[PDB]
Amino acid sequence: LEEAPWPPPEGAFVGFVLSRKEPMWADLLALAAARGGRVHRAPEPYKALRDLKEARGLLAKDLSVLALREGLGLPPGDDPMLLAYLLDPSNTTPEGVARRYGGEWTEEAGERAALSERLFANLWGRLEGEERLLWLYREVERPLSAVLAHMEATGVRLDVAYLRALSLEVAEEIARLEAEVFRLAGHPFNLNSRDQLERVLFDELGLPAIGKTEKTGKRSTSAAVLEALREAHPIVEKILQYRELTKLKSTYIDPLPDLIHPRTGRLHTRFNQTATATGRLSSSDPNLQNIPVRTPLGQRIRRAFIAEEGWLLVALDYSQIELRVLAHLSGDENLIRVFQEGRDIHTETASWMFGVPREAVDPLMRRAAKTINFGVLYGMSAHRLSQELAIPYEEAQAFIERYFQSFPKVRAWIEKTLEEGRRRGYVETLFGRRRYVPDLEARVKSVREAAERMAFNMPVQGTAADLMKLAMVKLFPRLEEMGARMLLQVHDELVLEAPKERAEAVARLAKEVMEGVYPLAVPLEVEVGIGEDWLSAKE
DNA sequence: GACCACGGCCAC
DNA sequence: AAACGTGGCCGTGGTC
Ligand SMILES: Nc1nc2c(ncn2[C@H]2C[C@H](O)[C@@H](COP(=O)(O)NP(=O)(O)OP(=O)(O)O)O2)c(=O)[nH]1
Ligand SMILES: [Mn+2]
Ligand SMILES: [Mn+2]
Image 1 (tube, rainbow, N blue to C red):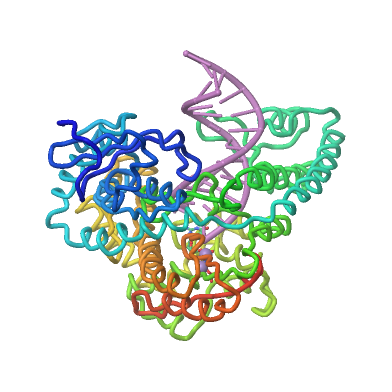
Image 2: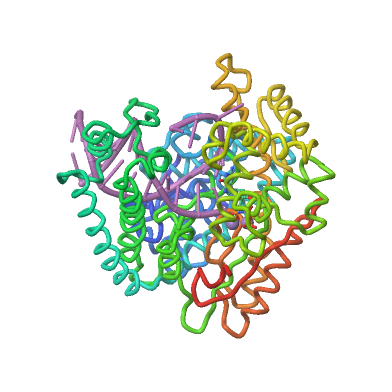
């Protein structure tokens, strides 16, 4: 391109280089812009930011986040990554999108800006006529990128002193468990090395190996295997306890306090918008979509996510979301009636499984029931279901028979979906988001049936992700007007932060927006709570 | 120091 | 482990 002096004209495509992938932590090393066969390279990138009216180009959200960090309202606009991702969600990285649609991802801002210009022109051309993907682009993904930029720049408050103290309490229990393990094994070794554990459990001790690992064929030490040996030998029980605590300490308790940002005082994740095959978001650096919740220690970790002084967290989570979606997608009159009758299939499976009244279904029982309901739904084998439910193969098999018999329109939908996937090569959501599933016609059964399970899961999970994204796009302006903040999305949940005097109003409003986002054949229902911390707000 | 594969496991 | 699906991060073990 012909080098032109900064600033660029309105509507130019930007390119930028970060010192590191995380925008909230990155030094802006270079800034450039391309338009009309000219490239503009900034002499000092931080100052040059002030000249742009929007971030338009590859990874626009990231630059917008860094501008917000610097106090600049630079919203993300067009991003060829989002076009590629809607065309095919295996388009996940600039490296790949460039290597597919006519360019090369380098480490120079001017080139990245020129690349952004050429990739947009191309991908926008490929989407000419794809009016459903163009709707999703204009009405969901492009506006959503602005929402995520704000969430990423806002962050969440963390009770650091609390987690530091918890680290010590957990450490003392870890050393106790290790001591009991070393004693049972008769000698010390590295519990964290599954190779060494394998030799202790299955060679030194006489324990039987239930299963083997995929790539290398070692005898597995997975929880599922160890659960199979739970009473086979006590050491197993302590191993499982040691695993839980080191997992939570090494992944959450210890890393998270060290990630608080100097200027904000808060913790900042990244919401990756072109990372999943189904249309879901993902979260990284750190992942705040897999913060513990299930166990008593996990609940203690979640209590560390707290509201700024004078504010409250509002947590909203859709009810039985993919089951309602399935009702709408399949048109099963029976499943639809379940939700018009306001029943709850998780608590009912729970009461089935645990032989207890729906009044006696604690959160652990529901989460166990969730896994059964979605496991069975998405093709789980009777054999595993017997293992999980600790119940004979004949029973587990009739569980699956009952499940499907209750909702016959479902299996008709599954086979319609798969037939469509074979014919067109892709499956699609309610709003037309696509996943290409080429292995539906594979000649190896195992490969083909795996593709089948991925293929007919995507319309259900991807529709739910579509609804949530749309809700976020609708809800966000309403929150800014009430002086509230959107902090986190966890697939079918949102965490907000609101002034204490507005929290009831924000909660009421957010629940209405989310439930009425896009009426289906069944009502969407949202559970909402309010609390000083993430855990209190979900109750 | 940078990467990577693997097994393993947290969440939805 | 396994004919549930979708992610990202851990420590180990390893290379360059
Ligand atoms: N295939 C599969 N999908 C799952 C699993 N866990 C979650 N999902 C998918 C399917 C779920 O619909 C969705 C949201 O997960 P939740 O909010 O934790 N559960 P839900 O909204 O259903 O019930 P309620 O909110 O009343 O507790 O994530 C799983 O083990 N397997
Ligand atoms: Mn839910
Ligand atoms: Mn949820």
